[PDB]
Length: 98
Length: 48
Length: 143
Length: 48
Image 1 (cartoon, chains in turn green, brown, orange, blue):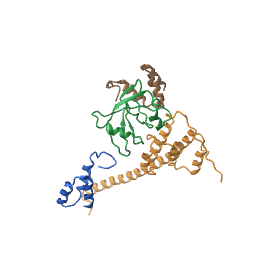
Image 2 (cartoon, chains in turn orange, red, blue, green; image 1 turned 135 degrees about the horizontal axis):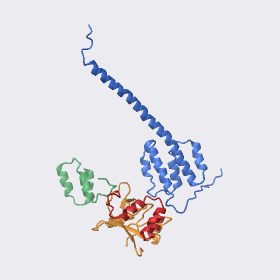
Image 3 (cartoon, helix red, strand yellow; image 1 turned 135 degrees about the vertical axis):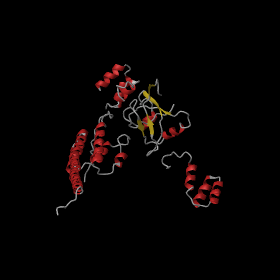
Image 4 (cartoon, chains in turn green, red, cyan, blue; image 1 turned 90 degrees about the vertical axis):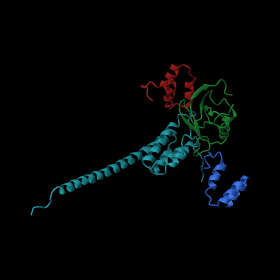
């Protein structure tokens, strides 16, 4: 029960290290709320055709049903304020993502 | 990471890393993900 | 003077594998700015294809084709082209056409300089031979 | 330790390190540490 992450033109092939640098600054709020938790983690999904930032937050069927949970490595934030590292570790097909 | 070392204890992960080199659009990858059987995805990958 | 923004820009709906030629355009631009540095290479790091900040791809292709040294006429020719792969093909062609000349000049410079080195290095060997042959014996003991 | 990395989870410590460069007499250091409010010590540091 977390908002979907904004891939923003970044394909994350299974078992393929990837970096995500969204231009929006609202996902960092979610990144700071997870720091007090014992185990740090993030989930990974892929976006469908006709990318739209308003559709990622408005409806939840746009995203495909497959998903890939994985563990966070380390934050850097060299240039932007949202420099997360992503990985394709555990593929999953959630019964219902909504 | 070679195939002659027999250290590829989880082949699916290596095959996914190898299939990532394909230039097919992401949607096509999702279509490959719909496949459950292993030879179906292998044949689709070869076709790709 | 009458004018109208007849900026045609058709592109396929499926936009996943269509940016791969762009990937080759930026790879050729990276090879042109690495082997033939014209401008700083930090600007290529600022505007990347992986950031998804390319809201205007036509502009990105034009900015990438601008590093080419091809004559202005060629630029007009690229604008005459209406299809998108034709202009991408022409931009890559401009890049390679410059690239061959650059590679020739670079190979020639290193080659010519190494010829100068083989010149003077053999002269250093000849100098050592003389010096070592001059100071062996008593050298001008005829009288 | 820059301000754009947001890795300064304890700004007070970085500000103290920056105030350490000041050449003010030891007494001044003790007096600035005695101050409890955050803008009071910061303003005293700026004036010094």
